[PDB]
Length: 210
Length: 210
Image (cartoon, rainbow over all chains, first blue to last red; front, side, top):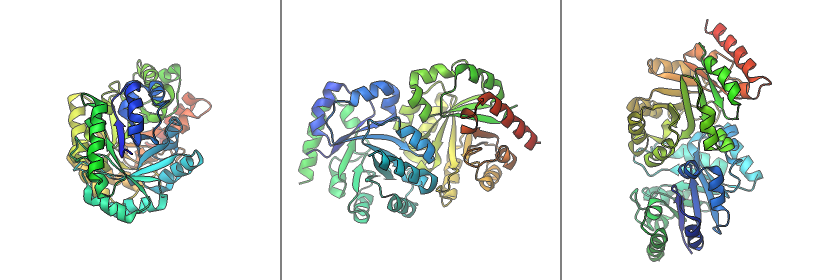
């Protein structure tokens, strides 16, 4: 089975997604897509797809009232990504209660892949993650050391890792470091043949994993 | 002149906004609105309005490529709010270059109003703000001490302060502490008569300011 989550930050056709459906673990929908296609067209695009997870990633980072106002308009999603750094009281606690009541999963951003991401607040972020107890956490694919350490610190958590391909991540390295799934965007959706690239990347990963 | 920025996180009619136009400094457009009305309807709503600033607040917090992909679909806006905590290299630096080239202002989130917002990284966030040199910064209206201190640390910056009304901020207290404008949402858009409430709040503020 595939370990890839498609970061659909540019539109792909419905027919393409239907082939990918059984060769992806999930699809991660971002603001760039929702602003390109619009909300209605975005929902239509995702309807028939049989993937384990439809994740909405608007990198949620506001007070609870606002984060809840956002996600209630995105009920087609199974899961949602929010930032850990915003903290618990009056922000993530309120969102967690909401998602729990509405049968949605929460993934929290722990480490990002760009150089500008500060390492300085790992302890704070880990504490936030411990209090909230999300389904999963996002640990950057350029940040292999942190993936292994987060895997150590959170053995039962789903770990998802973006930054594979364009941002530097060599396919399968994040999974080998301890991630469950790799989030891949441009490497697929900007390829000549997105399905072919997904199949090639899947092959690379299942070789590395083994 | 008004010191109020309307946080339009729920739809208000075009006619209402036209009266407010000369009694607001700006209007802050969020994800809740864009997801409620949709993108096209949101743009239409904002077209004729004569306010100093149309600010889009999606609390931007991603890598540069993604933040740029978001804001280029929101060109109706004069200004954009992003989080400081995401850092500079490969995130805010790339967004700043983009906004500069496209004649847009950047406001960075420095302190939020909820209890869960950590105070621990004030130095890091201030450093990020110093490197980027945004038009403005967002300093929570419940966090009066921080407003005065940020005003001290950044004398020339525009300081905008949400959290007035529902979240606790007593109208005008943020301006008196050193903020330029107060961001107000529910107090206005959930009032029986939103125009009447804006006028009353404006009166309260111009009394306090004096």
